[PDB]
Image 1 (cartoon, each protein chain N blue to C red):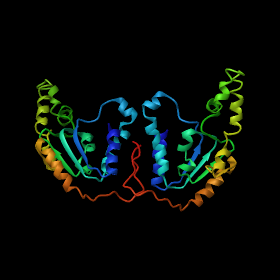
Image 2 (cartoon, rainbow over the protein chains, first blue to last red):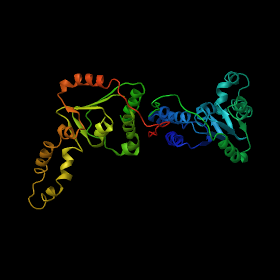
Image 3 (cartoon, chains in turn yellow, purple):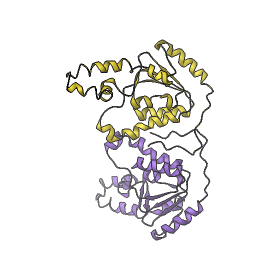
Length: 182
Length: 182
């Protein structure tokens, strides 16, 4: 997936074609093969290609955007110009399921002593962490998201955004060429 | 191997490190996996890297150099500055072994019908072709090799070459960046 998008992004940038990405990743496909085959190395090609791009860049998160997945899929701080998120956006370090495990390490400690029953407080906290953090507003407040608009507005937004970014002047530092991971 | 070299070559070029190539490849490793995994696509990277480089390039063929492998290996027409070859070099389209099958096609066709002895004919032809075409002089005469020198002379030759190409001038086509296969 990464090499597919990485080369496509680089091609678009070569011929001044704006890049519009619709982001909905939970993360990276788990597996030893991915690692053995070089997911780190080969996956980094997407980051490089996108960070290097100078054409207009508009990213729309319709749903999931966790961990490094969020970083590679048109992250504001990766150079994305305009970033939009739908009400169903879930921008977070990781899923609430595995998030409570770390965040609520202590409260889960006594869970094996006093009121035991992991599944009621390891399931309640999950839904509590999910209903208070897993959303687009935490990122919207950090500016990582320009605005949280209703799905229907996407079409008109990209239209106007592409006009504003039309004469976008941008370039990379002086150098014969970069050293993208082959 | 291709990817391993490709990236390395690009790195040298990034930081102005002359690229010295010791050639001796009989070709590419056969196998369905090599294909399925994308040898064509990934193999190109070594080609891309070298063709892109602008740093002094010196190539020395110590023995074998067949077909495409010959090309991708700092070949003269690939942009290499100085190409050297050892008396034991075997520069050709392919090994004399499978060459006779194409070249002396008809002659071998009448080795099964009329005068039949193939395998004692296919070994005489394989030797004649080998002793007349598979050598460093065909290429040297074409200019693809700057000179055919003794192995001992190698070290000193690379030394003067590096000096000559010291302040080499190489200008790559104006472009935000290339589109090397990923």
